[PDB]
Amino acid sequence: KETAAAKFERQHMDSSTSAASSSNYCNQMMKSRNLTKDRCKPVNTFVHESLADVQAVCSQKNVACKNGQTNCYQSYSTMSITDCRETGSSKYPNCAYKTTQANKHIIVACEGYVPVAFDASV
Image (cartoon, rainbow, N blue to C red; front, side, top):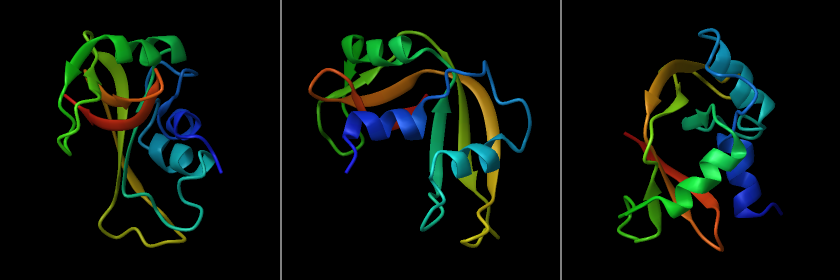
């Protein structure tokens, strides 16, 4: 087991770098965060901000989640984020990702009161 709060941190936090430094960021990070262990996770976003800044989103703008639940929150500010998406030819065990770096608002689901899912960036 792993708590949902802990899994969110593992899948979505990268407070160590201000941005992706190269187009290989996703290949490296998806591997090192255990997101390619038994299958390639198709889509994943890393947030280049402090843990405190991301947890704080849970007390910012309340919005609907994609699934219609009401426990999502949108960050007031843009944050540095890296979107990772599995390439068309990627085949487990050799997972391959496109890296996109941008400054976007994030939307997280919160429960309990901390983030437990990444809903989207805007």
